[PDB]
Length: 285
Ligand SMILES: O=C(NC1CCNCC1)c1n[nH]cc1NC(=O)c1c(Cl)cccc1Cl
Figure 1: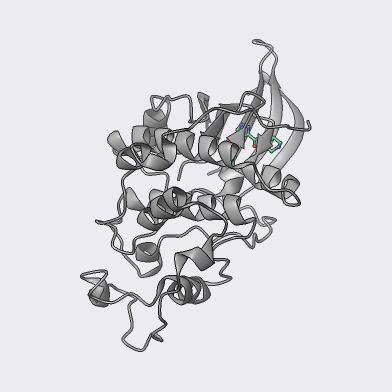
Figure 2 (figure 1 turned 30 degrees about the vertical axis):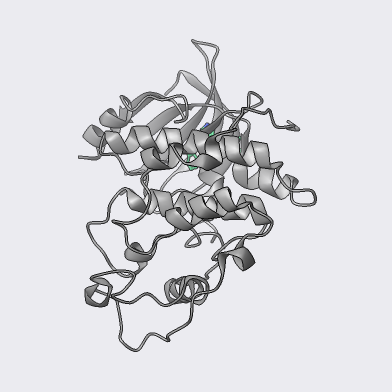
């Protein structure tokens, strides 16, 4: 750890602080995550999970009660680029390129039985090259200072909210669907501020789920017959001015039933991507 010089604190999460740092010996600039203290073996698997759309875990440094993760550094995250692009919006061909790349990254994860579990714009890092990468794949002492982030539950799949313990790769598809919608419309799709507010915002848009559209729903841990019964609203009202290929794909990423939800791999074959390209964003570092 003496091999690293802090440049600045980048931010803090629930169980770790992130710094920009310089490797005194490689010359590399890196993002360093510090966690105050199975975990070690699952991190070592993370070291082998290498893909162009996954932030490269360069090193894991266990010292006798801290764990440091050393990542490749990227300058910008999607959350801030969305904020930066709010007045004009992200051009569609860039939206589609970022969506395709995250689908590639997830296709890869998923085929190796790795779930992200917590995708959100602030976890998606971007470079000058038009690349977008998955970061902060989903123990330790809690940072007392961590300040609460409104966006926290906004990307949570409904089966998580309903108490499914043994949820699947489909939760990452749901999250990415929510991100897709938000890029298109420049508004969060389901901006809940508690778990029941998050559930009810979903129900209001997509309709309260029942056995017809989601077999087994009524038997989930936190499901209540007393949930209000909202009617589903038209998708054309939900993400204008997205074209029918886009809306068709989004609809399949947002299926209630985890088993009907489109997989990352099938999503890459969707007609929305027939004309995909790789534009480069205009970033202001
Ligand atoms: O945070 C980073 N860069 C900042 C983006 C916003 N502008 C300044 C630079 C970064 N660069 N490489 C990796 C990361 N961050 C993460 O991997 C990460 C962790 Cl370790 C924990 C929670 C979220 C994220 Cl994204």
